[PDB]
Image: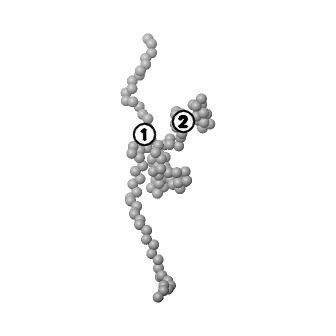
């Protein structure tokens, strides 16, 4: 399915499987890194760096 | 010979067309979960010391 910004507030969307439940979890996300941008998906292991650092990497990959 | 108001209706029927729910199967993903990165079998050292 395709959901919108206002339609997403009234529905449960698991990220990983085994997070899906029976009554809860109406939907599920395609990939776990769907939340991140195209450039933020080019940073390696962004999960183990602190966040202000991933914001500077995004701005430094464009210079 | 004209039209006059008749007795008030005693009830109302509202019709709509509706289909039903299937069983909950919840088939989340073709190849599901985040499959883990892993070791290539055997591998072997690709480097040796001198001497």
- Residue A10 horizontal/vertical position (percent): 53, 56
- Examine the rendered structure and indicate whether residue A24 appears above or below residue A46: below
CA separation, marks 2 and 1?
A: 23 Å
- Residue A12 horizontal/vertical position (percent): 50, 53
* Residue A53 in sight: no
- A43 relative position to B16: left or right: right
**SS state under label 2:** loop
Q: Which mark is residue B35?
A: 1
- Residue A48 lies in quadrant: top right
Of marks 2 and 1, the one in the foreground: 2
**SS state under label 1:** loop
- Residue A8 horizontal/vertical position (percent): 53, 52
- A61 relative position to A2: left or right: right
Residue at 46%, 57% in the rendered image = A23
- Examine the rendered structure and indicate whether residue B5 appears above or below residue A55: below
Q: Chain of mark 2?
A: A
Residue at 39%, 30% in the rendered image = B40
Furthest-front residue in this view: B1
Residue at 45%, 72% in the rendered image = B14
């Amino acid at each position: 399915e395709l959901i919108g910004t206002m339609e997403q507030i009234f529905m449960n969307v698991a990220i990983f499987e085994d997070e899906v439940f029976a009554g809860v979890t109406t939907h599920q996300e395609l990939f776990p890194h769907s939340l991140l941008s195209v450039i933020a998906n080019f940073i390696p292991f962004s999960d183990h760096n602190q966040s202000p650092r991933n914001m500077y990497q995004c701005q430094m990959g464009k210079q | 010979g004209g039209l006059t108001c008749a007795s008030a209706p005693q009830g109302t029927l509202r019709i709509l067309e509706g289909p039903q729910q299937s069983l909950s199967g919840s088939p989340l993903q073709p190849i599901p979960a985040s499959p883990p990165p892993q070791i290539p079998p055997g591998l072997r050292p690709r480097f040796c010391a001198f001497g």
